[PDB]
Image (cartoon, rainbow, N blue to C red):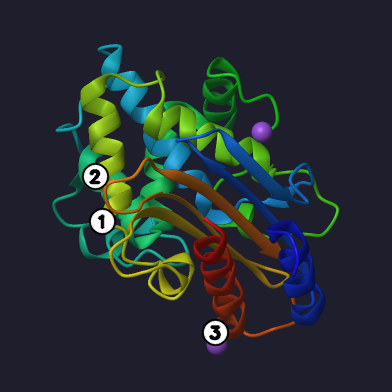
Amino acid sequence: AAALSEQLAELEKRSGGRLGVAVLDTATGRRIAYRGDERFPMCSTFKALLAAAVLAQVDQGKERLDRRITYSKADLVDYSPVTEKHVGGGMTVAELCEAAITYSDNTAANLLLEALGGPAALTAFLRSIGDEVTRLDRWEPELNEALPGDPRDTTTPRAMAATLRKLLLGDALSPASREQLVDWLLANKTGDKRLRAGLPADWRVGDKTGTGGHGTTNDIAVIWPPNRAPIVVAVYYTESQADAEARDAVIAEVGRLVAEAF
Ligand code: NA
Ligand code: NA
């Protein structure tokens, strides 16, 4: 037999690449990590944090979810499945948050960054809620480059699990904004082959995925088993030589290992 952290090490060994995991069981405070303090490229997982920062502006009376943002075809960057349909007519701030979170729409994220004040404003938001580790440096789509050894646009699994707990289950947002943020992650459409695929069917998942260069596949989540306190799980996987479906399977296996331990 072996501890969960040892099981994750064996998963890493047979999969190749570099795997980072942090888990927090909020019932007990049980915490476990594997490469929990190493930096990993966030890729789209930052969009959960971006939406939170926007909601904090709403909480402060500095932004409105129903504000309509009009843009142009010149704004469209790689991978924008929702915003590329709304150059005509635009989209509201809420719709952009939903697109960014549930479809990993890259232009939506840039438009929300523009509304917020950019990557330094998002990073400042994170410092203000006690995350001294996570950093957004670039805009879409360059922030997905995921160069090994590059500290730009990175987090650690422990920092991200702590931040996601703070945002979805903590004091950072108003009750209404916290509910809205949870709502968006519960509605995610990009995660069915990742953590969700390894968890029992009646566990409820709110998650945000990330995908990038140098074989990067990520998934961060708050998970509610039936009639039980939530578990926060952050998974970062990079420097893999495996194809996208195989990397999804690595994350799904982390989910299964977590479900078999907890
Ligand atoms: Na910790
Ligand atoms: Na593939």
Counting from the top left corner in percent of width and height, residue 52 is at 39, 32
Counting from the top left corner in percent of width and height, residue 239 is at 77, 69
The answer to whether residue 69 of the structure is visible from this angle is no
Is residue 88 rendered to the left or right of residue 81? left
Question: What is the number of the mark on residue 66?
Answer: none
Dot 3 falls on a residue whose secondary structure is helix
Report crowding for label 3: few under 14, some 14 to 19, many 20 or more residues within 10 A (C-alpha): few
Earlier-in-chain disc, 3 versus 1: 1
**Mark 3 residue CB less than 8 A from any atom of ligand 2:** yes
What residue is pinned by disc 3? 245
Query: In the orientation shown, which residue stands out farthest toward the top?
Result: 60
Is residue 143 rendered to the left or right of residue 183? right
The amino acid type found where label 1 is placed reads Ala
Mark 3 to mark 1 CA distance (whole Å): 22 Å
Residue drawn 38% across the image and 58% down it = 105
Question: What is the number of the mark on residue 187?
Answer: 1
The amino acid type found where label 2 is placed reads Asp
Q: Nearer the viewer, residue 151 or 141?
A: 151
The answer to whether residue 93 of the structure is visible from this angle is yes
Residue drawn 74% across the image and 79% down it = 15
Dot 2 falls on a residue whose secondary structure is helix
What residue is pinned by disc 2? 183
Q: How many marks?
A: 3
Give the image quarter of residue 136: top right
Residue contact between numbered discs 1 and 2, judged by CB atoms under 8 Å? yes
Mark 1 to mark 2 CA distance (whole Å): 6 Å
Which quadrant contains ligand 1?
top right
